[PDB]
Length: 519
Image (cartoon, rainbow, N blue to C red; front, side, top):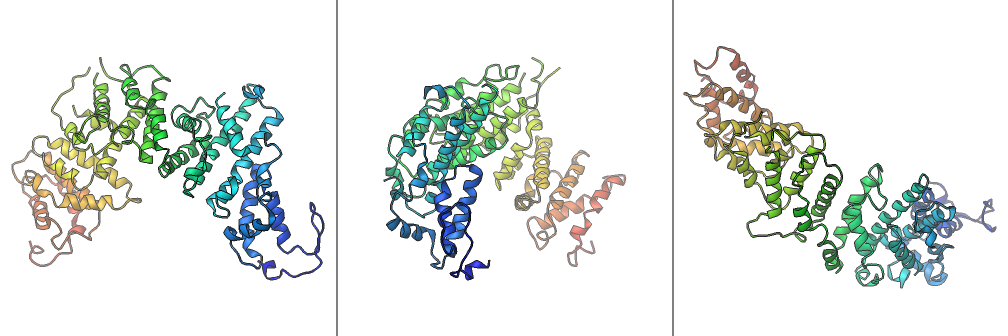
C-alpha cells in the first residue's frame, strides 16, 4: 500500500540474514526472494513464488516478469538463473526397498523443489524453455523413473512422500508440452520412452500397486483429472503413436472380452471387481480425454460398438436368473459404472428404448430392468432430447403402462434438479406439448377408468414442471390440450374426489379471453 510511493533513499534498518547495505526499498527484498526461491520446504515455495510475482512490478520500472527477468539474465549470467534450480544434491541399491532414512526424505524434498521451481516459470513466459535446458534434472528424474515401483510401519511416510512427486512430474510435462511448440522437439528421447508411457498406464489402470492407496482422500481425488489433462495435452506432440502402442495390448478389447466374468454376481471380491472398476474408470477418463474410438473402433459399421452392445446384453442377462441375483451396495455399483461406460461409445438410444418395451414375462419364486437403475437411464434420456419422446410416443396404445411409467420417471428426475439446469425441463415440456396426437386414445370416452386419472396426473406434471409463460396464444396443441382438459369433465367420470386435482390447475388457465371463458 504505502511504500511503493515512498521508496526514498534513507537510513533504514538491516534485517537478519544479509550483508549490510544503505537503503532496501524493494530491490534487496526481491533479490532475497529470487535467490532464496529454492527453499526446499514445500510450505514455503508457494508463498515465495507468489510473493515474487506480486512483488516484481512495484519497483519504479513498472515492468513485467517476462521481460525484466531476461533484462537481468543478460548481465547476471546464466548461472544466476540455474543455481537456484540446482541444489546441493545433483547426484544406492539400499534404497531399492522403501527406506525412511533422514537423507532419503530430504532428497525427495530436493527433487520436489527442483521439479516445481520451473513449473510456474514455464507456464508463465518469464523465461522461454530454450534458455533453461539448452541436465541433472532430467538425469535424476530418469533414474527415479527406473527406480519407482521397487520399517514397514514408518516407510509408508516415505511412500507418501514418493506418491506426492509423480503427479507434479506429470503436470510439469503438461506445462512444458502445451506452452511452446519447440518442446515437442526439445524434450529428448531419454525421458519420453517407456518410463512415462508406463507410469501413466500404471497411474490409470491398477494404481494400488505402486504405492497409491484407496484411503488417501485428497491425492486420489486430484489424480484422475490432471492425468486426463496430460492425456489431452499429448495430442499437440507426435507421441500419440507411442501412447497407442503403449496402451493397445493391456486395456484393449481382448482384456474386456476376457474379463467379463462368467460368474460375476457372486462372492468374488478383488481380482474381478476391483479390476473391472479400474478399467471402466480408465475408459471413462479416456472418454473424458476424447481418446476411446482412437483405441476401440471395435467391429462393424452399424454405429454400434459391439463390445458396448455386449455390455448391455450382459447387464440384462446377468439379472436374468436360479432364483434371483441378489444385490448389494457394490454389486449394483459395478452395474452402474458398467452402464455409464457402455452408454458412451456412440448414440445407443433406440436400442435402449426398444429394449424397454418388451412383452417377455419373468417367473420368479418383464419390465423390471427399468425399476432398478432408474437414474442414469433417465439422465441420459434427458440428454437425448427432442427425439426420444417422439420415438417413445410412436408406440402408445399396446403398452401404455410402460410409456406412462417412463414419462413419469424422466419427468420427476428432470423436476428434482430444477435449480441447476433449468433448460432441459422447459425444453422437455415444449417437446412433449406439441406431441398430443400420439396419445389421442386417452382423453376421450370409452376408456378403462385407470387411464383417466393417469392422464390428469400427466397434465398436472407437465404443467407444474414449468410456469404459465408459454402456454396460451396457441403454443402447441393449445386448443387440443384445452379440449382434452375440458372433456375430462364428463358425467360418469368421478364421484367427486378426482375432480379436485383438476380444479387445482385453474390458475394456469384463467388468463384467456372471451369465448371459452363463458364455456
